Amino acid sequence: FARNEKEAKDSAITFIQKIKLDKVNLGGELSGSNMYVYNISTGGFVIVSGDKRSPEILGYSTSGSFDANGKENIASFMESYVEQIKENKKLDTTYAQPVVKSLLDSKGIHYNQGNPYNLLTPVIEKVKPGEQSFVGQHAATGCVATATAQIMKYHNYPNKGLKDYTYTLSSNNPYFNHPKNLFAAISTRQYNWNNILPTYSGRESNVQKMAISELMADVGISVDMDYGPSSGSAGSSRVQRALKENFGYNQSVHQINRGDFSKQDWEAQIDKELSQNQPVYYQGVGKVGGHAFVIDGADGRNFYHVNWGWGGVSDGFFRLDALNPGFNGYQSAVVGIKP
Amino acid sequence: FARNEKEAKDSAITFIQKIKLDKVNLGGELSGSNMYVYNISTGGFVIVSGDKRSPEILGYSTSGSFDANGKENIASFMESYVEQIKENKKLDTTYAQPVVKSLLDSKGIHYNQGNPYNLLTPVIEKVKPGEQSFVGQHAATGCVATATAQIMKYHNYPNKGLKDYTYTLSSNNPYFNHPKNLFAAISTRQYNWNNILPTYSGRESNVQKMAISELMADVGISVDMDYGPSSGSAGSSRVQRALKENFGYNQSVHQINRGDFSKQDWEAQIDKELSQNQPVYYQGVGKVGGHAFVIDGADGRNFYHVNWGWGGVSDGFFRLDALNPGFNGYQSAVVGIKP
Amino acid sequence: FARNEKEAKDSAITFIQKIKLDKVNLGGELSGSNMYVYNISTGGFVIVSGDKRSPEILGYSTSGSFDANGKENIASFMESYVEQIKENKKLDTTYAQPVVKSLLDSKGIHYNQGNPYNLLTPVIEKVKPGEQSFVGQHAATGCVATATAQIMKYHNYPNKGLKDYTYTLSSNNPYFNHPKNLFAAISTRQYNWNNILPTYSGRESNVQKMAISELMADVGISVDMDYGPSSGSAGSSRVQRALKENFGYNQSVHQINRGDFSKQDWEAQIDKELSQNQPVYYQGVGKVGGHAFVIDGADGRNFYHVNWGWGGVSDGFFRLDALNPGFNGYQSAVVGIKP
Amino acid sequence: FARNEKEAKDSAITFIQKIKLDKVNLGGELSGSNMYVYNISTGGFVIVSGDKRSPEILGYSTSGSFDANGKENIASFMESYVEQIKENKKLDTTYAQPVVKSLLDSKGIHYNQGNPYNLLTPVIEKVKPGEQSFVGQHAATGCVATATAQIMKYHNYPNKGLKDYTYTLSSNNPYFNHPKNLFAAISTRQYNWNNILPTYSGRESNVQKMAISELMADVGISVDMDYGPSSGSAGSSRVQRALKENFGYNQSVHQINRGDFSKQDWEAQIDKELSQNQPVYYQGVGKVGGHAFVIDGADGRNFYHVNWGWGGVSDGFFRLDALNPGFNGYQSAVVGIKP
C-alpha cells in the first residue's frame, strides 16, 4: 500500500505526460515520506501521496515551483494533507465541477507580506528570546491581510473607507512594548486603485508603494493583526466583519465553516463563488491563528487554484484534502465577497 | 530576407522542439520587429532575430522568463543586438567551445538591486524634475555593485576588507544635496560569508540583511556609484581597481576591452575564465555608465550564460552579439577575478 | 534689599579674596539685574544674587569662565535661579556636607554636543522656517545624550551593548522628512573604551572619532532624541530606562523627582551618590525636554559641581536653587548609576 | 649653572607674584629638563629655562594654559628654545620696547585648523603606512593657512578675490591619488566678512561655516598646501606672494628673514609693525615646511604675543629666542600686511 520515491517520481512524470524532477525538501512536520514533492526543472511541480490508500495527485502546477520554507500558511496545509493521508491508512481499500481560470492571475495580482507591502506595519521594537533580532524591521503584513488585500484589489473596492478601527495588541506579544494600541483612520480613506498596483517589483515610486503599504496597514488592523517577524490573525471571523463594516462590502459577505458541510456541499459553495468571479478567502485554523490564502480558480478535475500571498511561489492547483471517502484542519472561509 | 512574426514564432518552437509562446512587449529602442521575444508559458523563453541576414537564435532559456521592463542593463544589451541586426542588413548573403553550467546558479546566488540589498545605500533626498518622488527610499544598489557582489559571494572573499574608500557624489546628481561625500570603512570589515546568504527572500533577520546590505554598500562606493532611484557607475575600470585594492583580490584581476580583440580571441578569454570556475564581470558602455552583468556559464554552442542581477528574471544564455561575420557597444569586462 | 552692580561686584571679589572682573552679558530671560555674573580675567567666575533676601553667592569657579550663549541647558538653570530670587522677594527677612572633587575632571572627561561627537547623528534635511539652514550639518548630539555619555565613560561600561532600540522621530520635527525611524544596533556593540577617549580635540584619527560618535549615536537614540540644530529628549525617564535595559547597568539605576523630597533629603541623595564615586544625571524640565547635566562633586559648603556637556565652559560649583528657606523647575535626576 | 625643578617652580611663582603650578609634560625633542613649563591652576602658565646661562622666563600668560601635544608649530618653537639654551652653555657668565595689546584678541579672532574651518579642505583618500586611517576626514587647514586667515580677518579684506590660483599636490603625498590638482576660483569671490566670524564654536549655521571654510580653502591653496591629517606649506614665501597677487593686499606686503638682521633690528621690525595695528605673519622653517603663527602684541618687556592658530591654547607672550647675547630656526616673517 505504500508508494515510494521511484514510484511517486513515476506517478509525477506520468501525471505530467498524461523531463527532470528535483525532489523538494520540507522538514519538521512534513518530514517523512507520507507525501512527495517534485519541482519540474523546466517549470512547475507535482505533489504526490506516499500511500495508495490516499489519492495519488494532491496538487500540481504546470509552471512555477513549490516550496514551503518560511511560508507557514503553505506548510500548515501540507501538514493536514499528511496527518490525513495517515487517517486513510485505517482502510484497506485503494483510492477510488466546471473550470475557472485563476481569477487573480487574470488581473495580474500577486501580493506578498514583505517590503513594500509592509512598508507601514508596526516597526518591531523588541527581540523574542532565543530568536535573532528583527528590531527596526517592519512587521510582516500577515497572510490574512495579504489574502484579503488581493481579493480587495481584484474588486478594486472600496474607493472610500467606511468605518474607522482600533485594537490593542495582544499583551503576550514579545515584539512590542505594552500597552500598544493601533489605529487605522479607514473612514477617511480615498483608496486610489490606480496607485494600488496589482503587484510590485520594488522599484515603484513613493505614490505606488505608499498606496499599497497603506491598504495592507488598514486591513491588517481591521483584523487585529498580531504583528511580528511574522503576523497572525484569527482570520475568517475578523475578515468577514471587516470587509462589511469597515470597507463597505456587500451584506453577502459571510463566514462558512468546513465542518458544517458535506464534502460535495462544501465544494459546491466554492464552485458557486468562482462561477461568479468572486475569489474566496480561505484558511486553516491553528494555534497561532488563521493560515489563510485565496482560492480563485478550478481545473474542473477537482483541484482548486490557490495563491499563497507570497508572490507566486507554490501557487497552483490543490485538493481541499487528501481524505479517502476526516481531519479538516478546522477549515473555514469567507464567501460572498463582493461590492 | 525579413523574418516575420509567424516565422519567428515558428523558429522558436522549432528551437525548443529541436507548447504555447506569448510574445513579449518591449518599447522604446526595442520597438519594431528587428527582433522578437517569446516567453514559453510552461517555462522559458527564446529571442529571435527578425532578419535572416543576422543569426536566428540570439538567446534562450529552458526555464524562467524574459523581460526588460525597468531593467536597463538588460534592455541596453537587446538594443545592441538590434542596432547590430541592422548592420547585417548591409550584406546580401544569409547567416552561416566547451560547456560550463551556470557557476552562480550552482551556488544558488541570485542578488537584486533593491531591498534588502539596498538597505544601506544613500536615502534619496530630492525629486528629479518631471519624475515622481522616491524621497525617503533607499537608492538602488546599482548593477555593477550587484554584478560585482554576486561574483564576490561566489568566492566568499575577502574575510577582511583591505583598504578604505571615499568619493564625492557627482554634482549634477538631482537626488541629493551637495556636496555629498560617501565613505566605506572597508579596511575595518570582517565579512562573514555565512551571514551574507546567496540570496534573500526578504524574511531574513537583521543579521542576514545587515550583512548583505553592507557588502552592497561598500562595493557601490568602491566604484563611485552615482546613486538614485537607479544607480550607475563607470563600471569595469572601478571594478577592477576596487576588487584588488579595496577587497584584496588577486593581481590577475584586470580589465579587457572588446575592441582589443578578435571575436574568437575575445571568446577564448571568457571561455578560459569559465574553465576555471571564475565568473566574469561584463558590461556594455553607455552614457549613464556601465550596463553590467555576470557571465558564468556556456552552452558550448556559442551561447553565454548571463545573470542580470535582478533575482533571476531574464537570466539565461545569450550571444555576445548578433553580428554576421560591427558595433560592439564599447563592451568590456573584468577577468582574472579570484582571491 | 536690592544688591546693585557695585555691590555685587564687591560681593564677588570678597568671595574670591575670602583682580579684575568682567561682567557677563546674558539676555532674554536672564535680562535684568536680579542676578549678576562676573568672569575673573585671570581665570574663573562668580555668580551673584541681585537681592539680599536670596542667598549671596549662587555659583562660582576658581577657574575657567561662565557663559550661557547658545547653551540652553545652562540658561534654563540660570532662569530658575532668577524666577526664584523673585519668589524670595515675598519675604522681609534677609538671607540666613562633605567634599567630593569633580569625579569627571578626575578622569579628564569633557564631552561636547558637536563635532566629532555628533559625527553620526542624523544629518539635518530641512530648514525650519524663519531660521537659517543647517541642511547637511549633523544634528547635535543633544545634552542628555552628552550628560549620559560622560557618566558612561566615567564607568567605561558596558563592553557589550545589551538590547537594540528604535523609535519614530516626532512628527512635528521640521528638520526631517517624515516618517523617520531611527535604529541603534546596540545589542551587537563591543564598546572599546580605549578608543572612546575622555575628550576629543578634533585631531583624532578615524578610530577614536568613530568610537565616540557612535557611543553618542546609540545613547541619543536610546532616549528618543528629537534631533535638530539642537537636540532634545524627555530626559530622566528615557535615561534611566535606557541605561538598564539597553546598556546593561545595575537595577539600582532609577529616577527620583525633586518634588518628592525635602531640600535636606534631596541633597542627601546626591551627596550619597557622590560619596560612592557615582556621578549624577540631573536635569531641569521644560517644554522642549530635559535641560540635563552632570553633578560630579561638591565643595562641602553646599555647592554642587556641574559639567554642562559643553567641553568645560560654565563648569563649576552651583547651588541647586536660590530659594530662601519654591519653584524647583520640575527638577529631577537619575541616580544609582553603576555597572 | 643648572636650574632644577624646585628652583624653576620657584622662579615661576616669583614671576607670577612679582597659587598652584602643575608641571606640563612634553616628550620627544622637548624631553629632558633644559626647560620647564607650569600651568597655573587658577589660570595661566609660565615657561622656565633650566640653565642659568640662558634667560629665566622664556614665556608666560596670565591666563589660559600651555600645551604642545599635536600642535607642531608650537612644539617646533619650544624645540629651538631648547637647542638654543644648549648653545648658551658654551659660555661661563650668567644671563644679563613699547606695549601692544593682542591685536587679534581685541577683535576676538581665534581660528583653528579643524572643523568647521577645514570643512572644505581635500578629503583624505589614502592611509599613510604605519598610521591610523583618516580616510573620509577633511584635511587640516594647515597652520600657515590659519595664521594667514586670522591676519586677513583682522583686516576683513579683500571683499573681492583678485586672481585665481592652481597647483599640483606634491607627488610624494600619501593621502591622495595622483595626480591631484587643486583649484580656487579666488578671482570670483565676494568675501562677506560679516559671515566670516572672528571665531566659531561649531553650532553656527550653514552660512557662517560655509563662509570661513571657504576662506580657509582658498588661502590653503594659494600657498600650495600639502594636505593631510595635518597640512604644511613653504609658508612665508607663498604667503607674501599670495596676499598680494591673489587677495589684493598692499605692495608693502613682503617677506623678511631673521638671518638678515641683528636682534635689535629684527625686533625693531616687528615692533614697528605692531605700532601700526598690523599683526605679523611669522614662522620657523623646518623640513615639513613653515611652522607658522601670528605675533600681534608685546608686553614691552621684550616678550611678543603669539596666537598659534589652535583656538587659544598655548597663546601668550614669548621670547623670539632663548639666546644669550645663535640658532634662529631659519626664522622669517611676512610684514607690511595691510590692504
Image (spheres, coloured by chain):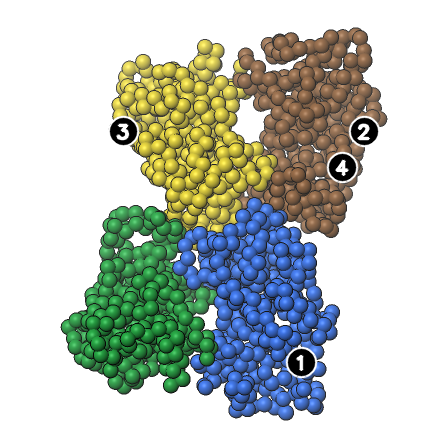
Chain colours: A brown, B yellow, C blue, D green
Residue sitting at the far left: D260
Inter-mark Cα distance, 2 to 4: 14 Å
What is the three-letter code of the residue carrying label 3?
Gly
On the picture, is B118 further left or further right than C257?
left
What residue is at 64 percent from the left and 60 percent from the top? Answer: C337
**Helix, strand or loop at disc 2?**
strand
Inter-mark Cα distance, 3 to 4: 64 Å
Q: Quadrant of the N terminus of chain D?
A: bottom left
**Of labels 1 and 2, the one closer to you:** 1
What is the three-letter code of the residue carrying label 4?
Ala
Chain containing mark 4: A
Please determine if labels 2 and 3 lie on a single subunit: no
- Placement of B89 over or under A10, stated as above or below: below
Judge by depth and name the residue closer to the eye, C251 or D201: C251
**Residue B159 visible in the picture:** yes
Please determine if labels 3 and 4 lie on a single subunit: no
On the picture, is C337 further left or further right than C121?
right
10 Å neighbourhood of mark 2: few (<14), some, or many (≥20)? some
The circle on residue B259 is 3
Mark 4 lies on residue:
A234
What residue is at 55 percent from the left and 69 percent from the top? Answer: C102
Mark 1 lies on residue:
C323
Chain containing mark 2: A
Please determine if labels 2 and 4 lie on a single subunit: yes
Inter-mark Cα distance, 2 to 3: 69 Å
The circle on residue A257 is 2
- Placement of B47 over or under A15, stated as above or below: below
**Helix, strand or loop at disc 3?**
helix
